[PDB]
Length: 117
RNA sequence: AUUAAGACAUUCGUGAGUGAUUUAUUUCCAUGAAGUGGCGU
Image 1 (cartoon, rainbow, N blue to C red):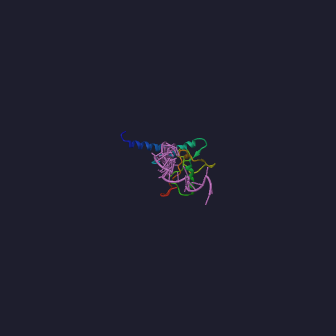
Image 2 (image 1 turned 60 degrees about the vertical axis):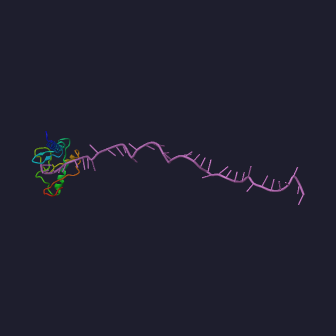
Image 3 (image 1 turned 90 degrees about the vertical axis):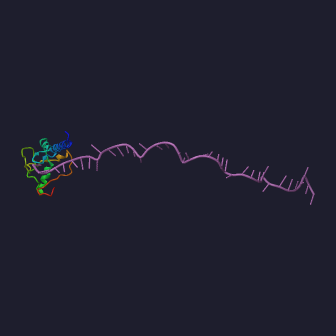
């Protein structure tokens, strides 16, 4: 109550955590909360999935492997981890995260250090 | 040799004295130095 710095820090850290959960999920320290925008677009009218998944697939199909010993999330389910699409036509991708703000640059860390997409 | 002759409308005289191109009039009104993170699933 008598120290404003801790109050400010906690408030702003909570704001960042909540907004990260809403928009792009939370993966820093061993915790993973799926981005709620992705889940909402998955569960609604004919499904729209991450544009980030499409860019990750495209950068996979050419070469250098992205860091992270996992796979893109293909939907909402327990450990619904996959790298590919079903036999019918591919998913209906879209710029899901543009509605909450244009980002103008996406950073991807591939398997070896010191180079980034 | 004739009711004739003689005679500068001339002298003097500064177009001058006093007089702010001045009184009044907003280079103003409008507008976010601001938008955005991402991978490490």
